[PDB]
Length: 298
Length: 4
Image (cartoon, rainbow over all chains, first blue to last red; front, side):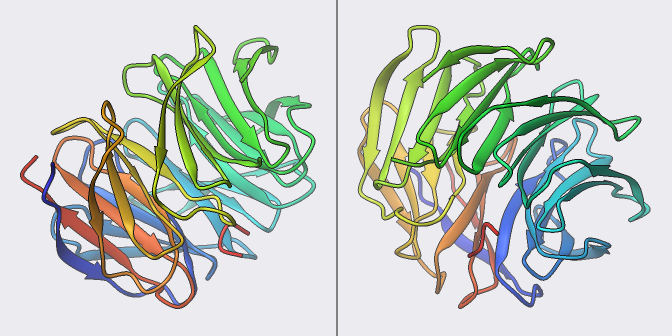
């Protein structure tokens, strides 16, 4: 079992926090919020660094480029923005979705962004131009998550239509189709997809074999698209937020709950795992509005 | 939207 302990609470957003993500270089944490802002904090000391503003409505997700120099944000204003983190400048506004943009991610090369929207499409955009390369007829209800795999050749998407689909990046073609599916992501090894469904379940899928290998239960997730993670820096865990205001940590192999992290006062909508240290960041909704940083020995 |  790990032994995560609360280290810091980061206050400052004035509405629900929607997403927290560590920079790939491990130095920063970015947080987005329904307050239309992105804030950047020191990953290790929790020190407030800067606020980044410019979206017209709240933000539901943010993601870092591989070099930790850029951030992309997905907003209710129907756009994504690419930001230079050191200057705080908006470099590009990505326009074309017809409804809220819900989720976003860079590829590993960081020349492409993928986004998912309430308009039920997945779009692939070029970073340097900020223009849309492809719009995929991906789902029949809002798209809850999009993620590239470890070489950027695949995209996984999920939706309130109950489907998870895997796409070929280069062609936009659907390669495989795997309750609303509220979150998906590829594993760090590239071999599995972790999928969350709004029936209080997380499931580990072998996507080559198209089979479910493991189910994780115990938490509450019936209403919100909560992020989950593979934690691989210490022991091999699955980490997720929960609607009972706790962070859950399961053993990836045994499926047992190994720890729950207590302290938030509303739904824990987002958790992120530090790329090299045993550090988790978590964030919560409107009755809480805070980010918590937790540290473990394994 | 994610927060609602």
